[PDB]
Image: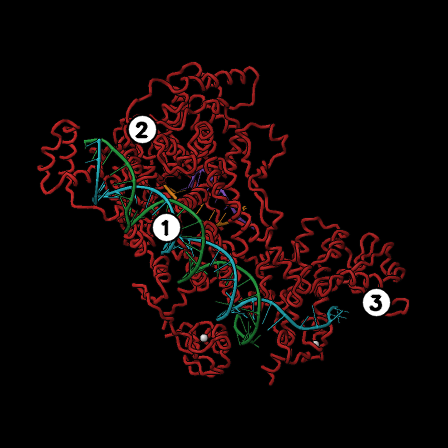
Chain colours: A red, B cyan, C orange, D purple, E green
Amino acid sequence: QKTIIQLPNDNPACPFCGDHVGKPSALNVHLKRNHGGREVEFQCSMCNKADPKAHSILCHIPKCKGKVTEEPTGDWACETCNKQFNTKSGLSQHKRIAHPAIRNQERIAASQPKPNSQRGKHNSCWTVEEEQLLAAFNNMFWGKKNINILISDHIHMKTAKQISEKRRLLGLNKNATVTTTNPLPVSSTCHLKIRTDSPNTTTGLKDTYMCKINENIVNQGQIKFDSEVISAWMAGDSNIRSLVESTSLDILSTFLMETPKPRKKKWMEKRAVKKGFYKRYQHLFETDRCKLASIILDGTERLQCQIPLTEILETYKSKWETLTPFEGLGQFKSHAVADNTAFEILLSAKEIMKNIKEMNKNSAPGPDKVSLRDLLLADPECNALEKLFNTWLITGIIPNSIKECRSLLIPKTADPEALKELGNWRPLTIGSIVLRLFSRIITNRLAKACPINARQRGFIATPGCSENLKILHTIVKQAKTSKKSLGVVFVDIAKAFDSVSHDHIMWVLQERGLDQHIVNIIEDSYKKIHTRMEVGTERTPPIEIKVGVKQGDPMSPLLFNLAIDPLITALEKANTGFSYGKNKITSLAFADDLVMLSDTWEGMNKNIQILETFCNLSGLKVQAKKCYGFFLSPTHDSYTINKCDAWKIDKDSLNMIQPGESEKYLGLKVDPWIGFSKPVLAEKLTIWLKRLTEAPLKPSQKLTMLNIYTIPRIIYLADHTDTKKTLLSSLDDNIRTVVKGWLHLPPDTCNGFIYTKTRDGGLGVTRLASLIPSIQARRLHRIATSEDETIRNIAMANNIEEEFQNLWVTAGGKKEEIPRITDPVSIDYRLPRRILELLNEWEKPAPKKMYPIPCNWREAEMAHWKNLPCQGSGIEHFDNDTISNDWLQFHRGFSERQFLMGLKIRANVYPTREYQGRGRTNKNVNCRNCTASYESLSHILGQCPAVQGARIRRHNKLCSMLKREAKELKWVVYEEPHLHTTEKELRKPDLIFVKEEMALVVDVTVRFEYKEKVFEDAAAEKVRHYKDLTSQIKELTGAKEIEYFGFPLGARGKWPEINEKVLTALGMPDYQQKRTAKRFSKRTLLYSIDVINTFENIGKNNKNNVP
DNA sequence: CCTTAAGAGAGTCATAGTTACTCCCGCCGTTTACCCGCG
DNA sequence: CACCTTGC
RNA sequence: GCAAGGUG
DNA sequence: CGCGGGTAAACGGCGGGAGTAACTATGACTCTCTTAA
Ligand SMILES: [Zn+2]
Ligand SMILES: [Zn+2]
């Protein structure tokens, strides 16, 4: 139980031990340190409100106004939680927000108007049968003699006056009539097969290649390829496959180096388990810690089930090889034709090198066991690479030897018992890295060649998920505002990349537009595709892939998108989607996942028939469970959700979303009621912080893991979800408290130290409330200036600009600085324009679009830190210094204890009577030891005597280090040279190292950077008091030249430039100069820590050991 | 061997904006179904 | 240069 | 493992 | 049948308006002061 601590409780007896520790803060200290784990909550006796945060209860203590628990009355208690309310206002508003499902139910119920007493109650007892018979007879009795006869009586219980009344209802002098209509759905995209011959000229690329090779041979161009293979191919050879495979084998053997052999370099006590855990974690931190970060944050490991290889085999054998007869795509047509000129260009080793650069070097090598690193080692020039690549390309016969690839099962689930199934293993297929690179090259060529529909936002340059999500949210809000019904249908097909039959993609490509050369090339690429299933100590014998694009091959994305395009096309051909403005946007698309946006339930039905047809042609399998959907319907005031019937996707009730229900989409939690469900950020954040806290991750390591791995995870959702500043502030507060506890910093520490970057001296901790707004604004602008004019139009009419302005302000950007969202952005190329034209487009880099930023915040915290009187004294020295801050990131050798107190000293908040005095006025501050008014930290430095000997020993120790280095640099030692100046008094300088005839007078000193002129005053004193001298040393050392410079140092470790001038006068190379400055600074800081330690001993440990 | 000084953030409640509608809503105008004598 | 997302 | 995007 | 004028009652169309639970965001204050492998 959370032990009830009904504050005020002065010094209570800690119930976990019943020990009177002290003030409630002292009780905290107790429970936190020794008696943790046990539950405890401070109670606010008056209101009895309880909080695990003492501070908060103290905040009550004045604030709290008694027993504030009484609940206001009323006469509308909202059914579910019976929250009494003043009026219906409060009631159905509680429905609206707190209890919105029943609210939708009420909305719909009242929605059914069924009002109609517009008739005015004039209605009477007429019968429709009598009305129809009267109408027919009057048609028969049109003003023709003996007109009533039947009318008067055959309508029993009526009068001619009543007949006149009814005629006055319909026809006045006569009867009347009515009419009706009916709509229909749309289908039949399953016709008109188009393939007749080669889409592009059979030799269109072949003829170009022949011409280019002729030009090269005549002019000896730089295009690389084996001569004989191309000679035979031009010669119309029959066994070209044989020869091309032979050359392949030879060149690959060149790349199949002898890859370097692995060069990677009672009795029952639980201590072994803890030591192994600590060892594992420390090693992973030393080694790759991405694995460590996953293990910690996810709380997981690596899994390898032992499911009978026989089974696993049967499954995948029957899956990959299993085929389905592709009938065709009927009328399904995609975007448009594809240009072939993009391929006319021949391969350039420059381009291949380029592509190589854009590779995951850290990738497991294929069966060849050859890596991109290995590959480059073989040919860092891509000369032979272009050679054999062109060999194949021009020939068109990819070697079958390289085809063999390795397959991997990914333990999708976490629970072992779930893992037992085969459904928790996404199969990864990895082939020859050479094959991978060639594939990506051709893939880039194709992607340029074949244009996809804009609506597919997957696997392209545009920023995908953000665009889709923002568009969806907008659309929803826009619709609700516009008071117009709308239907939403999520779709998801299984085995997106796996069920695909090679034959159908063959077909698809046939009509797109492509030279038969590349056609056959791709076929061969996907022809004779064997692989083995790597598992533990066994890889299954070969399996011939006949269905499913090779999982891992760079092509698979492009090919899949290509096969899917026809669907998107046909859907737009329906042009029955939501008529946003002019555009009738039908559906969005990302990779495989897609939606459907019609305007009427029946329009959506039409869409579904189209989809069903598509599956029929493709033989694809969609399911209601695999899919979700929901409908919107406007009211007089608000919108109703799902008011209509659930659909019948694949003849199955599409699972509908109801208010409050959320279904994941691109990692989000789309809720029709509120668009995106508010993400559970605090919960995941706290969980992660707990996991980190409770591990062998010595504090510095905790901070490193945090800043470098944890934050991005939360960044993604926080930014992608419109998040308000207050919640971010709360999260930042949580993080600050947690880290401060981690490193046992004093509570009141200034934030600026925490937030400022390590390079600037700070802890480099993110400030979500300051960072997320900038990311959000960047996304906003990025989407605004998109290529899809539709997306633009949408955002524009959705007046995103106001949000952009507001964010830019919120992130801290100035109103004037607000860029005009319409204007273009900076388009860099990482290449001098000259070099840019020098090369070809295929070798051109990717022009990433630089975007504005509202402001820099790290600098903001830095500035505020500077402004601080106490915690911010002398720090400005450390701004934009790449030397002093270094140890923060590479505090090697420092003891964790030393390092932590080093943080404190750097912050000037170390325990000292002044520090204990700081803030709290009424106290004593006199330096215990000497007399200093404030028992400050600087008086220690020099003023405070007791040290004396230690100060001297440290000083001459540093002098000794520099001396030791001196002889190493052939600087003749003439240090500690007792002198006798004009006063014949000992002015022994630190160092007078002589060389040739130059004698280098030096003055080693280390001063705390209290003021700004510290070191320049030092130097002025150096020269000033030294001055004269000259002659005496001139003859003593027999030197013809004498220096007088100094060597001041920052006590904290600040490295002035004067010592640097000494270094350059010494002749040290620049790189060694930086190395020396860094190391020397760390030594300075360490010996300062020693000074501290000593003093702290002096009096404290003196009393402890000697009472 | 060197320096003058000495809150800073944690935290709660108060109050104003503002969302999101929703509620609604009352008042005047329209529509309905008859209601009545005549060529 | 390290991380993160999604989606296979 | 692959394709993109983002972040310091 | 034709053939006019009356009917007066929902509702809906429209001006507006009026309110509001519950977030979101500043403002104004007060309390806080010791544990490294
Ligand atoms: Zn209270
Ligand atoms: Zn002193």
Disc 3 residue type?
Arg
Instruction: Please report, as a chain letter, where disc 3 is located.
Output: A
Residue receiving disc 3:
A987
Report the side of A961 relative to A87 (left or right).
right
Residue receiving disc 2:
A504
Instruction: Please report, as a chain letter, where disc 2 is located.
Output: A
Q: State which mark lies toward you, 1 or 3.
A: 1
Q: State which mark lies toward you, 3 or 2.
A: 2
A258 up-or-down from A1103: above or below: above
| Residue E10 or residue A488, whichever sits in front | E10
Residue receiving disc 1:
A638
Q: Residue at x 32, y 49 (%)?
A: A641
- Res A133 → quadrant: top left
Report the side of A1021 relative to A806 (left or right).
right
Disc 1 residue type?
Ser
Q: Position of residue A733 (x, y in %)?
A: 51, 63
- Res A1098 → quadrant: bottom right
Between disc 2 and disc 1, whose residue precedes? 2
Q: Residue at x 87, y 70 (%)?
A: A985
| Residue A582 or residue A524, whichever sits in front | A582
Whether residue A687 is visible to the viewer of this picture, yes or no, is no
